[PDB]
Structures are given as structure tokens and as C-alpha cells.
Image (cartoon, rainbow over the protein chains, first blue to last red):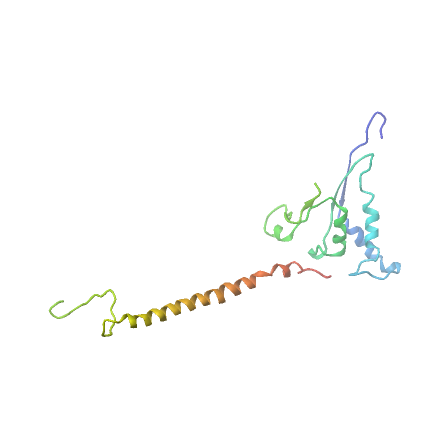
Length: 116
Length: 69
């Protein structure tokens, strides 16, 4: 807060937040943990929630967040993209078929949703 | 009729004898009608039935294409 002033609106852009969990997978076994379903660490959901819960906006100040989320092997069922869905308000899903068809942007009109 | 050729143009001509030849024209009528009936019996049964069954449930397979589960 600046005196005689209000809170400042803050933008936040993150690029491939998936790499954050990927870098946790690389050091998972070395920390002595049993691997989870595919190859991920057993603490995937918790270590994603701890990060994702600090991005919200509170009674003082507002944080508008844009995040690109990678999708391994074009598979929206993979544990990390499938875990990330619950933490977002508007989800824009890109498709490889549409991009290969020449349409840009490749936003899939049937998977894009929003609470708004 | 011409001096060497007689040409008879008939609407419906059958080679049989009597006046009751409806009783023999009915045989051709029934045979051709049965063939035309069995045809539509085969058009629906073979073509339209199978060719929709094949296209019915393809989408359920293509969506799980990349899954590692």
C-alpha cells in the first residue's frame, strides 16, 4: 500500500509450470521415495497445490495469472495436466489437429471452458 | 402391312392362345414383384444396416489413442 494510494494490480505470467513438477520428478528417486503411478513422485498433488495456492488474490490486491501448461505426448490424461485442471478458472486447450489444419490460433472450441 | 413384311406393334403381347391369358400374365407379374420385393429386402439388410454399425462407435477408440494409463 502506498499512502494516499490503493493497491496495485499485478500481472503474473509463468511459462511451462509443468517443468516445475518435471524437475521434481528428476530428483524424486534420489530422495528415496517409491515411484507413483507412471513415473511421478508420490507427492505430486501436494507439491503442486502448495505452489498453486499462493497465486490467488486476497482482500488486498489482485493477481491476474496466465500460465502455459505443457502436455506430455499430447495426452491430456497424464497425471500432471490432469491434476492442474482443478486449480484454474479458465482453461484454454490447444489441439494439434487444428494447428496441422492451418487454423491459428489452434484453440479447441469444445474443450475450452470458463466459470465466467 | 407391306408387300413383303407385316409388322404388328402391340401394347402388351403374349404368345399364348386363349382369352384368359391374365392367368399366365399373373405368373410374370408375381415373379417380377417377388424379385423387386426381395431386392429391397437386401438393400436395407446388407447395406444400410452394416454401414451404420461400422460408423457407430469409432470415436470411443480414437480418444484413448495416446493414453499410458
